[PDB]
Amino acid sequence: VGSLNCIVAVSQNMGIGKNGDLPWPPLRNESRYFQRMTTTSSVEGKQNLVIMGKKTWFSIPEKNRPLKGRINLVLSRELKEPPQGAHFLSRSLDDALKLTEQPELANKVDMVWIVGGSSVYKEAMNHPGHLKLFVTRIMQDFESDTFFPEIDLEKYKLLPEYPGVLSDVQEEKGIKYKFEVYEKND
Ligand SMILES: NC(=O)C1=CN([C@@H]2O[C@H](COP(=O)(O)OP(=O)(O)OC[C@H]3O[C@@H](n4cnc5c(N)ncnc54)[C@H](OP(=O)(O)O)[C@@H]3O)[C@@H](O)[C@H]2O)C=CC1
Ligand SMILES: CN(Cc1coc2nc(N)nc(N)c12)c1ccc(C(=O)N[C@@H](CCC(=O)O)C(=O)O)cc1
């Protein structure tokens, strides 16, 4: 309906997950920022849609499932029905976007947030149209078993600044990271 965005935390070796979880120790402020970006809606009486693969759903601690104040959609071709706590189930990303245009959700949804995993990001990244990437750069190498797709800099531009995103290097548990905003339109 509105804006389509991807949001991801990545290590310096482009790693995003190791055994069902994050490769680095928990960053409470990095988690808070994911929460704030995905939950805030720009319009009244409207909520954001969160779209994720099934192994991403199963890595959110059970006590936080479904993500509060968000419409939670799970992607999977194997599942018969949405997992317990999930609001919707889709077989592909074109179908999940064909769904926000149903009067059911059409008047309800402001932004669309892709929250992973690899397979999901890869396809959003090739979708034609306006898209923004929200990338947290975790500045060290971490042994990973799942990786973020290559960002094609001939198509995506790094923005010099973005409203409500801090520009400086953060530090938490001795780890440095920074926030980037990339924009495409083709
Ligand atoms: N650092 C960060 O930002 C992030 C880290 N993570 C972490 O990364 C890993 C999650 O990994 P990843 O394996 O890539 O998993 P996904 O969450 O992408 O799960 C893959 C499953 O999702 C379904 N699916 C994925 N893409 C599609 C599609 N286009 N259409 C329909 N179904 C699809 C399929 O389920 P089926 O097999 O049922 O058809 C596929 O087997 C974890 O280790 C997690 O903690 C996750 C997201 C962000
Ligand atoms: C593995 N993922 C993907 C994930 C984690 O960190 C990220 N950080 C970024 N920048 N992008 C993402 N996609 C992720 C997640 C795992 C658990 C929760 C979760 O518990 N979220 C609570 C967090 C609340 C909190 O930390 O208090 C929420 O309300 O959003 C979210 C995402």
Image (cartoon, grey):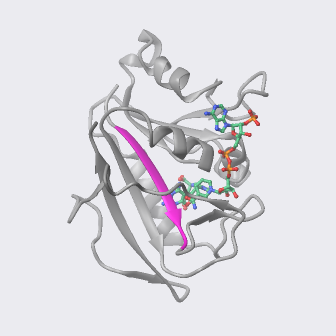
| Residue 101 magenta | no
Give percent across and percent down for residue 86. Answer: 66, 33
Depth check: 183 or 163 in front? 183
Task: Give the side of residue 112 with respect to residue 59, left or right.
Answer: left
Depth check: 160 or 167 in front? 160
Specify whether residue 117 is in view.
no
Residue 87 location, quadrant:
top right
Q: Residue at x 49, y 18 (%)?
A: 99
Task: Give the side of residue 103 with respect to residue 129, left or right.
Answer: right
Q: Residue at x 53, y 71 (%)?
A: 28
Residue farthest to the bottom, as pictured: 174
Task: Give the side of residue 74 with respect to residue 185, left or right.
Answer: right
Q: Residue at x 79, y 28 (%)?
A: 78
Q: Quadrant of the C terminus?
A: top left
Residue farthest to the front, as pictured: 154
Q: Ligand 1: give its quadrant.
A: top right
Specify whether residue 84 is in view.
yes
Give percent across and percent down for residue 64. Answer: 64, 50
Range of residues picked out in magenta: 4-11
Residue 1 drawn above or below residue 146: above
Q: Quadrant of the N terminus?
A: top left
Depth check: 15 or 164 in front? 15
Q: Residue at x 41, y 15 (%)?
A: 101
Depth check: 177 or 142 in front? 142
Task: Give the side of residue 121 with respect to residue 146, left or right.
Answer: left
Q: Main secondary structure of the magenta part?
A: strand
Give percent across and percent down for residue 168. Answer: 30, 78
Residue 58 drawn above or below residue 173: above
Residue 113 drawn above or below residue 183: above
